[PDB]
Amino acid sequence: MAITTLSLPKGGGAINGMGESVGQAGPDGMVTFSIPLPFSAGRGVAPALSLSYSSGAGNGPFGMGWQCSAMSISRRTQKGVPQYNEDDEFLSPSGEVMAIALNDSGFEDVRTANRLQGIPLPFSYKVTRYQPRLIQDFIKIEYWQPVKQTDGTPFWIIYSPDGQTHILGKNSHSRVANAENPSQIASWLLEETVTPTGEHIYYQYSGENQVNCTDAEIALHPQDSAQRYLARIDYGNISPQASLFVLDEELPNLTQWLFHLVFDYGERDISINKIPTFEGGTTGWLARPDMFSRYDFGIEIRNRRLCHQVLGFHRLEALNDRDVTDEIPVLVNRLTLDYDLNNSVSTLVAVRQVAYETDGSPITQPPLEFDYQRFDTGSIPGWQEMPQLEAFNGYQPYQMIDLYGEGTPGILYQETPGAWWYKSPQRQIGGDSNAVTYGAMKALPKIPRLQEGATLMDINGDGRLDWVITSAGVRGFHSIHSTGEWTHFTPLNTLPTEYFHPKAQLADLVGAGLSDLVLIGPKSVRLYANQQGNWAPAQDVTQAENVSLPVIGIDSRQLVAFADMLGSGQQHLVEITADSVKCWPNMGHGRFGQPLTLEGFSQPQTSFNPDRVFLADIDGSGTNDIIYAHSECLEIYLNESGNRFSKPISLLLPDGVNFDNTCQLQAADIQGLGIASLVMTVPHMSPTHWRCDLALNKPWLLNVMNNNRGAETCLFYRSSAQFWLDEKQLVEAAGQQPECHLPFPMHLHWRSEIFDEITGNRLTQEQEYAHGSWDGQEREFRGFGRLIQRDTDGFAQVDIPTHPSRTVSWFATGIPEIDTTLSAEFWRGDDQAFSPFSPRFTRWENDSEAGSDVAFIPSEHDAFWLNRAMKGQLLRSELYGDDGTPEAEIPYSVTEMRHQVRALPTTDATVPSAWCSTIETRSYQYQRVAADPQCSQQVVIKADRYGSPLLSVAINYPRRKKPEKSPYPDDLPETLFDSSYDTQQQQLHLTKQQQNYFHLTNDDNWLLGLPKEQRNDGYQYDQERAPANGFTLETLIASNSLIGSNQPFTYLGQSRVAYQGGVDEQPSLQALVAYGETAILDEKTLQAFVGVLDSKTRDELLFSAGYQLAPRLFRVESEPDVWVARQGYSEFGDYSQFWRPLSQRSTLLTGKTTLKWDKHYCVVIETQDAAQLVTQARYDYRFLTPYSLTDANDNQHYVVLNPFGEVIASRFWGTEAGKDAGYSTPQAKPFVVPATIEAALALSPGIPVAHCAIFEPESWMQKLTQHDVSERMADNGTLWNALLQARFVTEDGYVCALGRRRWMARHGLSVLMLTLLAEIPRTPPHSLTITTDRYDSDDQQQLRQRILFSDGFGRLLQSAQRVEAGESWQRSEDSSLVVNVSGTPALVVTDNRWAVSGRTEYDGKGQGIRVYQPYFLDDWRYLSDDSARTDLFADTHIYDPLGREYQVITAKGYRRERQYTPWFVVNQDENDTAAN
Amino acid sequence: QLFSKTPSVTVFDNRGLSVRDIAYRRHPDTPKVTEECITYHQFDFRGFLAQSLDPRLNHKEVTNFSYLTDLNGNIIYTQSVDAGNTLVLNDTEGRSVIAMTNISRNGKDDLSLAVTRTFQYENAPLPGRPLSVTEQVNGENARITEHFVYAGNTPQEKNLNLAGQCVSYYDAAGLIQTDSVSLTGKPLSVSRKLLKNLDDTNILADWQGNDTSAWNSLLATEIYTTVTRTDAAGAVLTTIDAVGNQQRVAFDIAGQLSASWLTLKGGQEQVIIKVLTYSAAGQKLREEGGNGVVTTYTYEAETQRLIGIKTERPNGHAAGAKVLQDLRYEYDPVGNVLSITNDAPENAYRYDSLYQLVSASGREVAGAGQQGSDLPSPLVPLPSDSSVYTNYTRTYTYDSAGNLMRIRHSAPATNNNYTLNITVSERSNRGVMSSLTENPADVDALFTASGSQKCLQQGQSLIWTPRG
């Protein structure tokens, strides 16, 4: 290699899009989809974020469910509210707790310091380096503190092993804290980064303000300012600096960076017909409809701004290095983003990429739509009775809780002589999975059950109920398993209270899951002390005396709750009259804030009563909603965004029923909806129970997305708790004892459909899972132990059967108490397969010779943390295709994957830090034939303190002993199977690969992963030598090792590198390389030369073929040196030149390149070589891309690209045996490429360009206009406006993709719509290429008019060239083939003849099955695939599940057969397959 | 069909390389046996094939190949019992350096028969391109079989687009002075000069010493240059064999050939086509040359298996309506022919399951005699007779390994029946019709150490040379 030649753009391409990146699922179940960002690489490094939706994501400036936020360092709050003290605790953005680090001597990483990057600090200063509880990768981290912390602020620094280095919280905007007293720092935020080359990127934050705010917000929220928004990124520093700039006094001017990303919330004109500007004017950033706040760090956290346009800015003349005065950067491109807006939520309807013509005309990519599940109550259906329940409530006749890890409760009427009648929900027989009913009771052996404060709850946070004991003197409980295991009595040094009055019993605000009791009200605050069901002392505090006092128990036509109308999860205090309602801001420890009223409710207060009132959230946000009863109705008030309330919904009661003080409403998820269905009893007649219907889905899940290229996502999603009831039900149909270690409810993605936008084929994909798991101490989702994964393509047909994928897989939950059980689940139709990969644990020591580890058994505590760290590690998988066969039960293959951990000392004494490695794989390949897989194993043997694979091995295994008959069909002559065995099978083979690195990591440096030395050597052995379980690492590391180094191996080879710069071929700071080292020959490989040569000629031929002696690596005791070459000789300036390539070489024996740069070293402008051929290029710095080249003959070659940065035309001109030749200089013939394909269909010979191309992707959607629609509807455009508001039509007048259905649904509109559309087909994304037969020196340029058609999924569909008039097929206006009445193609003369090629019956795996024949056609329009399927000849590709055509059928029905086995593959042709 | 159950298989080691060939081969008229049509393949611990065999040598227990290799394991010096031990050797950069073959079978084999060629290159600053190569007579003199004289970068070389380029491939048979080139990189002229007398069988065509100031003694008076002009499409605008022959061509709206006109030496240039029709596959369909005949061709459009061809002088031709031929042809599923016929009487064919041919009966002209190393006289004039091409049968036979046995024949119309039989080596492909020698082990003595034949058709004079 050498630094690249001066190189043209592609000179060609195809119609394709972007963002096409929906993600696959995993054992977390939190499906998420991510999209990359349409902005530059800068000079080679640039901000590299990417956006995402996640099923599990909350709200943001990205709207609900979306994420592209970069990173910061922050506290935990799941542990409750911060102290703003030393003893708070803090988290990597990597999601792990950040302990202080330890040194060799097990002391902390700390000191006072007075320099950084050698920069002597403007003060005495103090620093501490930090360590996570878990390492994936070994980033060095330090905290920074003034020696007197009040003097300015602390801050943070990051050192990735690759040297990439980052900083947090020098500045207020780069910081988040209590706005009133920032001494309560919340967080430090990333602000800038430097490359080893001294490039930089900087990241702006904008703080909150009153722009677009109003009186109510002003009254309520005078604290917003600590809020931040990622308003701009900028990069390409005007001049290099390898240190951070923000070491300085203050960062240089805006001009000193050259690329920018700019983000705008509606300030600049969102109109497609206005290109925005780098300056935004003064319209001011909007505030979202659905504003709210967070609280969770013990502070106000107002949330207001969502972005709608993002802008790429290039300082063009500075990029040109030409001019700098008033170089206001060009808006290169405009991402544009569109949201659905509602009183309580907003989130993306769509996005689109846009660029702009120099006249300012926009050009557009296809949009990309979304439609998350909209909560609606126009939906809501009527009532139903509950025969399953119909009398089992009404004051005392009801009792209820989930104990059995159910996620939904058993009814349990249960008393002092109590029945324990655990009447519990069972699947209904028949009907859908969702069908359920309550079955038999079951009484059980159980506790004293009386006079004890005897009550339902899990109090310790155990996932197990803790049936309470608190009687006279006697205190404790008994714990109950999901198994009904009432543990023995639990005295625990409990410290329960006086309970003086049970009135005002606190619970929540201590912290989620660790609820605790405090009797309290005005002017005072009693204190909790519960930890996990134990207590410290309780205390006294109060919130400030000005704060309004929430107060309990006064029945004066009013209600109280600890309830989160705000949907934070903090069940805030609320007081509720018939006229007013008030909620106190959570302040956790000892406090609340001054309360806020909410609005949107009243009742006739003289007619009111307390209760008649119900409090469940029903919108699914968390904002608790409200119901009132009425003489024949319910009134339902729904919380506007956690701030106000909608107009109440009027629900008629069931006919003839009226609710009254006997009657009891309730809400619980009857059906497995994942949100509470409506429930009641009227204890008046003997039957009493009803439900009311509500909805079929949990709301706001993404549900579907699309591209206007015609994609969809049919997202399907199911209760994991339903899954548990199913797993339960089916394994009880297997009579097994069930115990899902996940008790805990959530609703998870489950399946999807995808569709062929043109052929109407489709595919199913399914996500399935078992052994739900949850943390019995930390309250954490511990994954599923097994996953199951399945799918099918499906077709309109015509013979080809689909065969569903089935596969099964296993993953660590980190809980032996179920993890053990998965060993039952492995298929063993095979049998001689070796023992399960057993997880294992080790610890490093600083032994001499640079340390070591001992593999070891640490404590069971440690193992708790070990297994939790292992959780999610993929253990095993086993993979099949589905059919009726006696090998449907046999997989194509199976794999298990061993994992191993190093445990690590920590300033945290309670648990070590750790890291894990997937140290092995082993992989049996059956081709679904169980008799005899091929198999291999791959293994890591040795690693360092930082886990590099210092030694590894891999093994292949000899064949099983000769069986007695073929398992394969008798189609093969038996001579095959009986000869299928060989001496060459009797053989085991074993690579060893060993290596070591450099580690420049003192002081500031942290350079890691530095390549240096490698050798491999091999062994082969007799099958009789190996143990029947195979060798393990633990086996062959032993002193007895069969592969012991005393055995004569084969030396497979070696490699090495030399770094350039002043470190003796070892890395310099930038780790630039002097050469790669490239071996050739030795006393083993000389034999070819030994066949021919004397010593002299041998030596000569080495020296002449380019080789030298060098030392041999990983040198064994007696080992001679080796002959080698060396390669890559290349040179660079320093940071002042950004170490750009100056001159570069493959080998000393051949020429060297020399490369010449623009002043900023943005690009090589020119190059010259060994042969001295100087080369010219000139570049459009919109895209930094060469529009011009010249060769050393002075031959210009030239290209132009669209504003989207894509090639659109080309030419070349120069000299020709010394005459001048080629096309004109462009400026000598300024020229217009036709604007349309319909225009280009009449272009003329002689244009001044060698080529051009023209395109229409968005043609897949029909185009409309105001006047076009008014020529039906004659309102003359207010309909057009309404439709655009309704997103039925794009701003550029296309029918919007989801719009098509969105509108015919919302407004019903009919053939009234079809009138605008039907005969204009969805026209495939398409283009015309042109190239010219001769230079414009000759006008008689024959015109190479070829159209082409593409998608986003298989890309190219078909392409056709205009050809000479004559007999051809004809395409119908309805796209059909035009036919004779007998269906023969209309095979008649056309002027506009086409040769038509590349069409085939494409498929979802990406190929096609039916390879269609080409033909002549009259038309540039796409013909119907229905006609093609009817009429057009094609062979059928019979892909296997591996995508391998085991068979082909000719269009004429003869076949080519094959079948595959691990050891051999059979094949047959059209003459031989003719066994019929 | 009995062709069924003849499949091919591949069978692999645990490395995953196919340890044998497999087919299932049947001679159809003796269908009880399917051959052991399988053979050994053997690969080293580097997974690179060390050996494979003729099965017919396997129980004879004698090996057939050698391979020798470097670090990176590429083949270097290598032999087979037919090819002989042979070398081509290359740079680190893969540039060729030397080439050798024709080494004997004792193992102390005689490289004085190496037939050497070796290669010579640019030096710094220039990138190291091959300026030359030389023969070397094995164990003896080297002579510069060519130069590739790279240009400089003068404005001249720019003009000619010869910047750095081989302006002078001084060569075997003389020089091509590459002397103009296009901006499209296409050459535009080159003086092909022969040797000073190209029909001199022994003047070197080797280019020793300083420069052509010497080799003017060796390059031709026959300065039979070529000159060229080109489309931007790179298709030929015109080209001119400077002795006076020249060409022009034109194409359809897309790029298929529509016409050409070709100057014979110093003459006018004239079109070749009177009427043209292709298939949409770009294959032919219905054409009339300056010949003025209708010819047409008819095929399976799915495959272009030509079912037939017809020719006539058309009605209204300068010589009126006259059918000249009407051939018809027949094919199998994979597409092997089975028979052909024509009118203005038929012929038919058979193959092994291997598609190895076994029969080719048809009609053949009386009086031609049994085939020798000859061409007969033509029948003159063209027979209008229905019969002189009398019907016959002919057949083919073949080794287990890749070698023929015999051709066997009857001419029942004349009883001129005969068989041809091949003598062939015990141990190699060396083999010939049995009247040269009948001895299948004497026969292997008759071939060079590079396996070319030592002497001609019946022992006549021959010499093989460098470039083989």
Image (spheres, coloured by chain):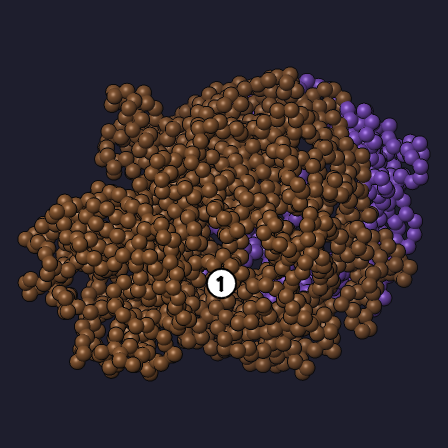
Chain colours: A brown, B purple
Residue drawn at the location 20% of the way across and 72% of the way down: A412
* Quadrant into which the C terminus of chain A falls: bottom left
Residue A1229 to residue A388: above or below: above
- Residue A157, how many percent across, how many down? 62, 53
- Residue A676, how many percent across, how many down? 25, 57
Q: Amino acid at mark 1?
A: Tyr
Nearest the camera: A993 or A639?
A639
Nearest the camera: B157 or A121?
A121
Residue A721 to residue A267: above or below: below
Q: How many marks?
A: 1
Q: Quadrant of residue A483?
A: bottom left
- Position of A1092 with respect to A1371 (left or right) is right
Residue drawn at the location 39% of the way across and 68% of the way down: A538
Residue A1019 to residue A564: above or below: below
- Position of B389 with respect to B302 (left or right) is right
- Position of A683 with respect to A1138 (left or right) is left
Q: Chain of mark 1?
A: A
Residue drawn at the location 70% of the way across and 34% of the way down: A1160
Which residue is label 1 attached to? A1460
- Residue A559, how many percent across, how many down? 22, 55
Mark 1, Cα crowd under 10 Å, few <14 / some 14-19 / many 20+, is some
Nearest the camera: A1049 or A177?
A177
